[PDB]
Amino acid sequence: IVCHTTATSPISAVTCPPGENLCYRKMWCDAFCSSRGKVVELGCAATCPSKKPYEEVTCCSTDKCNPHPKQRPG
Image (cartoon, rainbow, N blue to C red; front, side, top):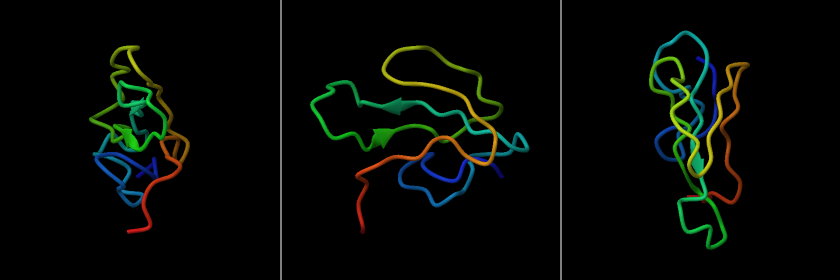
């Protein structure tokens, strides 16, 4: 119960796994930064181990912090 956005696809608030709040947000620019941007990771995987820099990354835990624009209305 925390991130209410992505995290393994479009998700739906899920909030990734347990951890009891927080959601490791990663990805955003696939890797081709060829525009758009709907292929992220922000899905938590414990207690946001931080991971690495690469493309995009972060770490929140205040209700959410891993959304994503564009997306798909279906």
